[PDB]
Amino acid sequence: YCKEFXATFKSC
Image 1 (cartoon, rainbow, N blue to C red):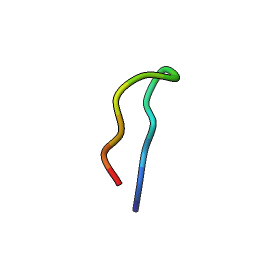
Image 2: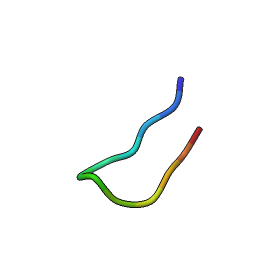
Image 3: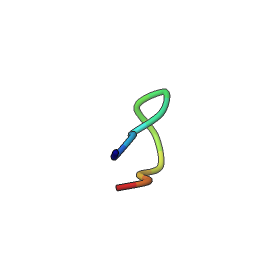
């Protein structure tokens, strides 16, 4: 799924 890591980049 998507992931905004430590409230940083986005890997959606």
